[PDB]
Image: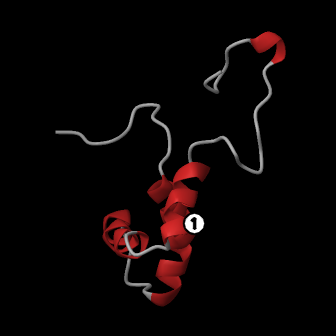
Amino acid sequence: GSSGSSGRPKTGFQMWLEENRSNILSDNPDFSDEADIIKEGMIRFRVLSTEERKVWANKAKGETASEGTEAKKRKSGPSSG
């Protein structure tokens, strides 16, 4: 029994959770394991603003973000082209 991810992309929760995790601890230092941090991140991520949700979900995607990707000669790479 092993759980994890194989070269899989990121989701809105992965971006926010990793961007809020630090904020979750600052308030509750008791959290010493990600398992406890996730259970909480979902509580705040599920109540996020109708915009924050769709947004964070679009950020993890990769496109329409601050940093973009460039492919010479419409070639293939680490980014779905």
Depth check, front residue: 34 or 44: 44
Q: Quadrant of the C terminus?
A: top right
Would residue 62 appear left or right of 9 to someone viewing this image? right
Q: Quadrant of the N terminus?
A: top left
Residue 58: horizontal and vertical position, in percent?
A: 57, 50
Residue at the extreme left: 1
Q: Quadrant of residue 55?
A: bottom right
Depth check, front residue: 15 or 73: 73
CA neighbours of label 1 inside 10 A, class few (<14), some (14 to 19), many (20+): few
Would residue 7 appear left or right of 32 to someone viewing this image? right
Q: Quadrant of residue 51?
A: bottom right
Depth check, front residue: 57 or 77: 57
Residue at the extreme front: 50
Residue 14: horizontal and vertical position, in percent?
A: 48, 55
Q: Read off the residue under disc 1.
A: 19
Task: Please determine whether, in this image, residue 4 is positioned above or below residue 44.
Answer: above
Residue at the extreme bottom: 27
Q: Which residue is drawn at the image coordinates 73% and 12% (left, top)?
A: 75
